[PDB]
Image: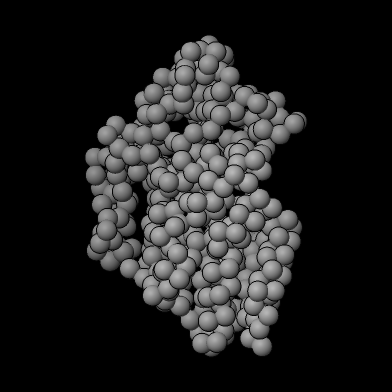
Amino acid sequence: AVKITMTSGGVGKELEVLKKQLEMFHQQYPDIEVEIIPMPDSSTERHDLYVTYFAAGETDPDVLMLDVIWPAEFAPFLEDLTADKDYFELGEFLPGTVMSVTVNGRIVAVPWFTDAGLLYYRKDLLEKYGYDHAPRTWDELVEMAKKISQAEGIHGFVWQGARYEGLVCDFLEYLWSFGGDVLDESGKVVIDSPEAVAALQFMVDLIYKHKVTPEGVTTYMEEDARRIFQNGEAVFMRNWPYAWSLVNSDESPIKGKVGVAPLPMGPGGRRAATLGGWVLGINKFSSPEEKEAAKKLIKFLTSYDQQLYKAINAGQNPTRKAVYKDPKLKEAAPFMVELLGVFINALPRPRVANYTEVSDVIQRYVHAALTRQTTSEDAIKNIAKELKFLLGQ
């Protein structure tokens, strides 16, 4: 009776699993038909597609698949879900993911699946040199990296330092773990702090002072760091969860020699991880019967059973805390079970409507500091100054 549309958003296995999920949904809700609107695989080619839907205020699509950095931009056009927070059981989701969908105190989407930065390390090299544990502080990681890389003739620590969005993600992990922040609760720019100068200066020192990170890191993206680490040429790597399937596969030279752990903490700081992933929103311009049908679909897809199903069959990490404790997940994918201790410290990038401009500014000055075109102090001061203009403060 009621027909709603949804955007995807998918690779071949991940979309075939979505089709099965929609089948199961239709069995439980026979009066609701769901139609998938095919969407560009590029994140950029698709961000402008949606703004067109809300430029012209279309009634379709009803259910939006949104990148975790888009809620603030789309919030004026998304159905307010704050009254439905218990209907969706948001208290049982990872705290970072609930933050990522709260825009100016309004629940504006529902977390679906998630990602976050973590630390990969050569487990064999750590025990060969007498290290019981993954580094718990950043200074501890420098000490391990320096000792082991010099004795083995490899690099210490590879990560993402090219001028792109990935650099922002790496930088926020240093900033947060050193005790700093971009915006506070009220949303005012607080990045101009000694913690932030310390965090950025630490990134520079990894290259030029301690020499545990190659100078080429200023050109590295995810796969550049991965290839070096996978070939045995780095003790440590910061990356996303996707790399585990690559570096622990059969044709991988380091298979069985890789451990994973949260990123380290800074002096007097936290452990931190930058949140990635996708969320589900409702077009506020759809008819009320399409919206009500859309809420039922989102409740179904983000339920415990469906997050378990998607995790086992498509490999996406759940957003509900409890799914990580399921015994079925522990035997089907024990690596995913280990990510719980990472995801409890994951935080979202700043929730601002003009995020892409905020990111451009951070990329510009952070990369300038990594290339020694400016000092950490000047980079942080300039970021704070520009962000205050961009945010009207």
User: Where is residue 285 shown, x and y percent of the image?
Assistant: 50, 85
Q: Nearer the viewer, residue 310 or 47?
A: 310
Q: Is residue 252 above or below residue 358?
A: above
The answer to whether one can see residue 373 in this image is: no
Asked whether, in this view, residue 391 is left or right of residue 206, the answer is left
Q: Nearer the viewer, residue 29 or 297?
A: 29
Q: Residue at x 56, y 29 (%)?
A: 259
Q: Which quadrant: the C terminus?
A: bottom left
User: Where is residue 376 shown, x and y percent of the image?
Assistant: 32, 38
Q: Residue at x 65, y 67 (%)?
A: 8
Q: Is residue 379 above or below residue 108?
A: above
Q: Residue at x 40, y 33 (%)?
A: 264
User: Across the whole image, how many numbered discs are drawn on residues?
Assistant: 0
User: Where is residue 102 shown, x and y percent of the image?
Assistant: 38, 65
Q: Is residue 341 above or below residue 4?
A: above
The answer to whether one can see residue 80 in this image is: yes
User: Where is residue 62 shown, x and y percent of the image?
Assistant: 57, 79
Q: Residue at x 54, y 51 (%)?
A: 323
Asked whether, in this view, residue 94 is left or right of residue 300, the answer is left
Q: Nearer the viewer, residue 91 or 34?
A: 91
Asked whether, in this view, residue 228 is left or right of residue 170, the answer is right
Q: Is residue 321 above or below residue 25?
A: above
Chosen colour scheme: one colour
Q: Which quadrant: the N terminus?
A: bottom right
Q: Quadrant of residue 32?
A: bottom right
